[PDB]
Amino acid sequence: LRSRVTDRYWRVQEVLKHARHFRGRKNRCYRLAVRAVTRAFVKCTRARRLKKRSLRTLWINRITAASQEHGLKYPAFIINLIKCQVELNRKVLADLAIYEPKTFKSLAALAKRRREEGFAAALGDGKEPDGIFSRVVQHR
Amino acid sequence: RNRIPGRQWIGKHRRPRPVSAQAKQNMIRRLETEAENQYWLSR
Amino acid sequence: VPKTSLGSPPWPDIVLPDPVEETRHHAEVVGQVNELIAAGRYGRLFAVVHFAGHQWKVTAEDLILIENELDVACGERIRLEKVLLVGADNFTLLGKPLLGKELVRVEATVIEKTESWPKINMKFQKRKNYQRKRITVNPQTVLRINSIEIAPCLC
Amino acid sequence: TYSSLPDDYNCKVELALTSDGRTIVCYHPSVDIPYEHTKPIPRPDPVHNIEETHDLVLKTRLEEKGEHLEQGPMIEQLSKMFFTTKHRWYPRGQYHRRRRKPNPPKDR
Amino acid sequence: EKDIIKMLGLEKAHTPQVHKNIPSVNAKLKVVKHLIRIKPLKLPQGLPTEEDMANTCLKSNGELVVRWLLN
Amino acid sequence: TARGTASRFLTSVLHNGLGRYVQQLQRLSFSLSRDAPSSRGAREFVEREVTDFARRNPGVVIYVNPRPCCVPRVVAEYLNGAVREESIHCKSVEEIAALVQKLADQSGLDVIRIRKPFHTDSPSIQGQWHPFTNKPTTLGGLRPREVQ
Amino acid sequence: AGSQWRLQQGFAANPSGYGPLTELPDWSYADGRPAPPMKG
Amino acid sequence: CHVARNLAVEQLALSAEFPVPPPVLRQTFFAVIGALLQSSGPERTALFIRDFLITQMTGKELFEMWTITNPMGLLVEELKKRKISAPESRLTRQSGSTTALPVYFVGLYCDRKLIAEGPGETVLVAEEEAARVALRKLFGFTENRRPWDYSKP
Amino acid sequence: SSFSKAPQQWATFARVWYLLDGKMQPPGKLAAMASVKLQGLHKPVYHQLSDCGDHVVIM
Ligand SMILES: [Mg+2]
Ligand SMILES: [Mg+2]
Ligand SMILES: [Mg+2]
Ligand SMILES: [Mg+2]
């Protein structure tokens, strides 16, 4: 019983269909395409992991730009927005920076007011004075 | 021009990399945590 | 009084208003925004809402794609409860950390309950004869945000 | 009157905290550019190719302007004009011209 | 140290575990005290009864609230 | 691979769900066999759950064709004109039901990489950022080193 | 970031810890009937 | 034709030359509309119209479908109607004037009060855009306007 | 806000010319802001693939 492979055409096409957009003999020759496609998939996974970091870095850079446009630094902006219990991630903050300049300016003003309140509190060292925006609201 | 003989962090002559204030602060924080741990493990 | 380079801090002195006057001004501003909301002088509203682990900035007649399946049928309406932020051309309400359900209401209809494109996940190790190829198909949902209403109940 | 940020650039922020304390409101009316902060529109209209003898030739004297340079000087002029480098204006080969998407997707 | 951390139920990181204050477990906690953070379990509202088991939570400061998110 | 395959943006057919929701599945054609062992699941589905599905979804025309075939198939035709052919070869009745429900919930668009998980028409409420939105105007509109 | 401030105030170091942003149901039907509970 | 081809009216329309040219498709769609009007009520037919034709205006602009030619003329006519004297064009902001790609902002002031502002590559284009923005603000067809009401009255 | 598509795009991606006095100023502290404005890291619409870059004139 001599058994030979008859679907080698499709076995080769299933790999060559992922290399048609390559350059050189990697898009034609099978021996060179199996290696180029495996590296393509490994890079696809590594970049699926790295895309989140790249987009977070882009959002952070855009937030730094939109904050320095208001004369405020990014760490101060972020920490003083957190201290007001405003839980908006960097993606939403960048969306606001791009498409909502008034909302972002109000957020930056709130952050600056909270920073000034914290500075005044740390300078006075008085427990009875409490800022208006420095009040902490518990869960209801 | 300034070569490091042999490997970078193996031989008798290594890279003179110094300790930074960040690492000092991290070690001090870990030490504080461990001191609180050994206090809570006392009684 | 001597004036040197380090005799004074290198930042402008900040003066915060009186707490009583600040509370009065806050009451005035809240009343003004409440009158605006009651009169309905806001044109279009956007809302940052928390849903399915993510935060979405959505407006009326919007489309969003959630990467997981929901326990609803197509064409059904849904009230999104976690609204973090509402905004218009003239005013803006921020939650601490969320808004009130009686204050804002965001509604969205489920359009399409489909599957994502095949995502390839390959692991490979040099000269260890280790390759592993998997294909992921993620179930996804499409939501059309229809309306974002706001009530003048704002103290 | 008090404000964290100056109200001169496009909006007047007024922050407030609700009496309940669980909500922050911010009224930001837009800011219009005052008339004293603008300048009139400059109008430049001059026809020096007009002749008192033949207006039909005067009209062509302003339309017969032509100039042709080589690839090198043309690319240098384009680079000086658009404040870029010379390498962008050089053509590309068939391999790159054939692999451009004919119908790219469009949003909005 | 690996075996002590495994028998202490601390395989997963950043997840709190409740243990006794007896010398038997204090010995192992002293052995691996450089890998763990130890706090006292505070009970501001008492021990959770059988009708409050499903409505409890452990706050970040180390207290175990008995009535968590009522209604 | 995103660079190897095509792509598209998150869109809806005819602004679906905006005014009213319209089921995009137009017709569903099952082609099966009456004696082939591979069409057993399709036969049991046609016996049991095809009438309940037809009653739950009255907007889709269901055709059933018993014919001498070796591979049972289901062809979904959508309102945009898209044709999706799936194979129900050697599948349980529950798998047939799940596949048909997925085909009914789907919108008929191409299953490719969606660029953005969102789609906003005119997201520039209250304005859009330009380099002049946060800069103060000077008295007379004068340049930095311009003398009037 | 800001985890130390949250720890001082009593909330979780991560906003995804037992806060109302994650404990409450994120959606419900338009008629008001409750939604099925979340697996998490 | 887009709405009909997506609602599968072309597949049900009985007509030769299967492409069903735009006139025949319009005839068939509006015949279906008339059949719905004769069967159900005018309120339900109006709801159908609002759900299948007004939705096609989503994301679209006013002038994209109006296609006027003299925005400044139309604006001064509307202002004469509203009892306003005339808008004055003032160059508000500009970045570059000798470069190849300048940008200008032109504002329209009625009684020294800004009513609208528009950007452009040239001063004339900026003035035309400012006129279009003022026209949109006067007519109420703005971007931040109230979205269409899709409900059941 | 209610601009047309092309003028809105132009206004968003327009180039800006900044001036910078360098008299009695450190070259590195000048170059920091110069490079920021050159790359376009001062725009919330910034992206590495976009051509967002402003002109800087240092005197
Ligand atoms: Mg992950
Ligand atoms: Mg060496
Ligand atoms: Mg060495
Ligand atoms: Mg999990």
Image (tube, rainbow, N blue to C red):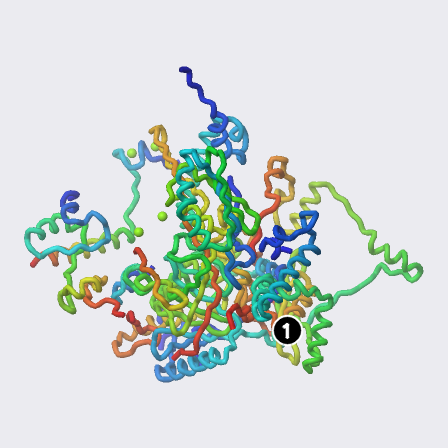
Q: Residue at x 50, y 41 (%)?
A: F65
User: Residue G27's quadrant in the figure?
Assistant: bottom left
Report the front residue among C108 and H48. H48
Mark 1: amino acid: Phe
User: Residue A110's quadrant in the figure?
Assistant: bottom left
Residue situated furthest right in the rendering: D53
Question: With D15 as the anchor, is G38 left or right in this view?
Answer: left
Q: In this view, does F137 lie above or below F2?
A: below
Total of numbered circles in the picture?
1
User: Residue F124's quadrant in the figure?
Assistant: bottom right
Report the front residue among F44 and C37. F44
Q: Is mark 1 within 8 Å of ligand 1?
A: no
Report the front residue among F105 and B37. F105
Q: Residue at x 33, y 29 (%)?
A: C128
Image quarter of the N terminus of chain C: bottom left
Image quarter of the C terminus of chain C: bottom left
Within the displayed image, which quadrant is ligand 2 positioned in?
top left
Measured as percent of width and height from the top left, residue A128 is found at 26, 79
Q: In this view, does A75 lie above or below A7?
A: below
Q: Mark 1 points at which residue?
A: H139
Measured as percent of width and height from the top left, residue I22 is found at 53, 59
Kindly tell me whether residue D96 is visible in this rendering.
yes
User: Element type at marker 1?
Assistant: helix
Measured as percent of width and height from the top left, residue D56 is found at 90, 57
Kindly tell me whether residue F145 is visible in this rendering.
no
